[PDB]
Amino acid sequence: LIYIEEPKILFAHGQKCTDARDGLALFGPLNNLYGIKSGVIGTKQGLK
Amino acid sequence: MKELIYIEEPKILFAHGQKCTDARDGLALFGPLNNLYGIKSGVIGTKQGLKIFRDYLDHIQKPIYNSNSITRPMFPGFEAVFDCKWESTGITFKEVTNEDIGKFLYNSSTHKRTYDLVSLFIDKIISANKNEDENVDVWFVIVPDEIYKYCRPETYNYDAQFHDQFKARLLKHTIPTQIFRESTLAWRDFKNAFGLPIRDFSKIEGHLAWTISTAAFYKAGGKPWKLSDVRNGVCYLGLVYKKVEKSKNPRNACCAAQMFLDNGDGTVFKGEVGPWYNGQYHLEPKEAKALLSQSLQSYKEQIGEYPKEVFIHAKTRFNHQEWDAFLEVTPKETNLVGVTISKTKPLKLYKTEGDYTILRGNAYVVNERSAFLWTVGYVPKIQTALSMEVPNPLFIEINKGEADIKQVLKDILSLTKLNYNACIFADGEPVTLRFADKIGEILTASTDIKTPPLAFKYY
Amino acid sequence: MRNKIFISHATPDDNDFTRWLALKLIGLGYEVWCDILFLDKGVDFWSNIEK
Amino acid sequence: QLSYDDINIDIVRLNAIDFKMSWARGLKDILEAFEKQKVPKEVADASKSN
Amino acid sequence: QLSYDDINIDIVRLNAIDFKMSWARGLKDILEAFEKQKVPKEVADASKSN
DNA sequence: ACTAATAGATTAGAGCCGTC
RNA sequence: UGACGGCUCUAAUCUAU
């Protein structure tokens, strides 16, 4: 059993960490987008 | 001895309540109503179609002063005026090399080459739309002047100009593409043989950059401005009988009606097509029950009732055999005021003093069912007439039905500011006819799309 | 010397009018301080207004 | 919704500048009163302040 | 749960930076306040945080 | 029977411009 | 297609010999 090292995933400004949750929570996504337009449907109650 | 009755010019609302009259300056000091976080700029073109944007795209972020701001006003910039982020970010440069273009441009058969040139462009756009990761809000096809210099007048009946076929082929994809040109975007580096460029866009680089910015703004779901006098529950319909003399059979002459409603949601749509050509710009009674119903079905489900009044504008008068079918499809609760608008009547008045035209807003009424509205002419806002002589005041007649002509006159003077293609004081003919015409030029070129009531942005 | 134009206004709502007014007022060349835009962070909030 | 009997007592004795019915008299009378009161200002911006 | 009326005397007068409603705008206002006050700082580098 | 027939009456693309 | 004008070049259509 040779151990295979845990890989890496990049984040904002080309940085390199190992956790998707931790990196985004502290670094952010790679591409820079401004806002997100949320076309939302559903029932009247579901709006609440 | 006759007099010219006057009606006041209505104004247009803007950001957080404020309501100015001019779209030029009511947008700079206030900003668009609905703010959007940013616009992703997708651009496709040749080698020279990219460095031009790399000059222009960030050029309108900074303020640029024309020769005089009174007549050709400057704008502080895209961020300072339109309240949005629109810069060199999200660029989707998709190089179509000139040799690749030349290998399709070298074909001489314009009936086949012109379709081929668009086919080079759309296949990339829909591929990026579906089979790619990048997101583009408004696409900027920078076709060089050479492409539309030569390609100008089942999948080849489209016009010699590729304008119609390119946009008609995206109706399946519904991606808003802002067709551009090198001349309109590269005025500075374009020079003629004698040393004086033909297009003198320098002074217009104010309110021209207003057009480009506001055209790219509205297509992204934004609301640059809305009218502040459009009445409640009232529908303003307009059909222009656009020729379908694009295919081999000239038997088709299909109109493209459209509506501009109360809530600012002007849902421009598609009329009905049928064998009525004999050269008569009228539609048979059977198809009339499919146009106005689809017009009203798209609104009765939206609001829950019938419209109050349907201002059916047209450049062509309505015969009885056409209007009779309109009666049964529509409810009696709405008065279908068919305002046949004519710009060919020979009425031209001049002033004994002053080198300008008659002040706009004048409505020389002829009788209860006729009028003459100077929606185009001299104004007190920009103190410059939107014409060179006094035009034909838009002959306004209640062709069928009975109503107050005065209530009709103001609304045509209202359907002239919501030109989400330019930045002018107002238009000379109602947008209910110009936007009803751009559908016909685009849609009726191709006869294989069962399109939804797509707004002007896709066209 | 008294130079800043005091826009005495409600903090949450009238600032947006002032973000139209003051930003235009800066555009017109007028000197403007506000409890939102020119108010420095970490100051005595009551005492800074008195100054 | 500013009823004249509900406005602050210090306000009523002073001529209020109208922004409600239009912005036109709002910023204008703001500057028009400034012009008559010689309020200090710098330059005239670019393009003669448009 | 800490109301604005339960703030201790050492920072009652001091203009606090709001984070309750959203941490992002508080972080931004932190940035602008430091820039306005010319707070000494080096080039931005998140590798140090990493 | 319609065969033409020259006009009024309105139409719109559609080049040609300018694009005050 | 940045756009809203302006006429102009051609053609088409129905009211009637």
Image: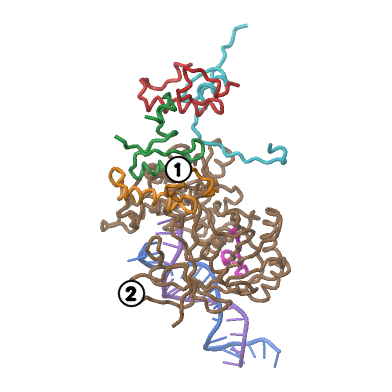
Chain colours: A cyan, B brown, C green, D orange, E red, F blue, G purple
Q: Which residue is the site of mark 2? A: B353
Q: Is mark 1 on a helix, strand or loop?
A: helix
- Kind of residue at badge 2: Glu
Q: Residue at x 32, y 47 (%)?
A: D37
Name the chain letter of the residue that bears numbered label 2.
Answer: B
- Residue C32 lies in quadrant: top left
Q: Is residue B183 at all visible to an observer of this figure?
A: yes
| Dot 1: chain letter | D
Out of B269 and B23, give the one closest to the viewer: B23
Give the farthest residue toward the left. B194
Number of residues whose C-alpha sits closer than 10 Å to that of mark 1, classed few (under 14), some (14–19) or many (20 or more): few
Q: Amino acid type of disc 1?
A: Asp
Establish if D29 lies above or below B157.
Answer: above
Among the 4 quarters of the image, the one containing residue A1: top right
Relative to residue B127, is residue B313 depicted above or below? below
Q: In which quarter of the image is the C terminus of chain A?
A: top right
Task: Reply yes or no: does residue B210 show up in magenta.
Answer: no
Mark pair 2, 1: CA separation: 52 Å
| Place of residue B379 in the rendered image (x, y in percent of width and height, measured from the top left) | 41, 65
* Residue under numbered circle 1: D10
Estimate the x, y position of residue B294 in percent, counting from the top left. 68, 59
Q: Where is residue B16 in the image (x, y as percent from the top left)?
A: 51, 46
Looking at the image, which residue is at 56% across and 28% down?
E21
On residue B248, which mark appears?
Answer: none
Residue, x 44% and y 83% (percent of image)?
A: B1
Magenta stretch, residue numbers: B240-260
Residue B149: where, in percent of width, then height? 41, 58
Foreground residue, F16 or D37? D37
Left/right placement of residue B89 relative to residue B339 reads: left
- The residue lying toward the viewer, choosing from C42 and G16, is C42
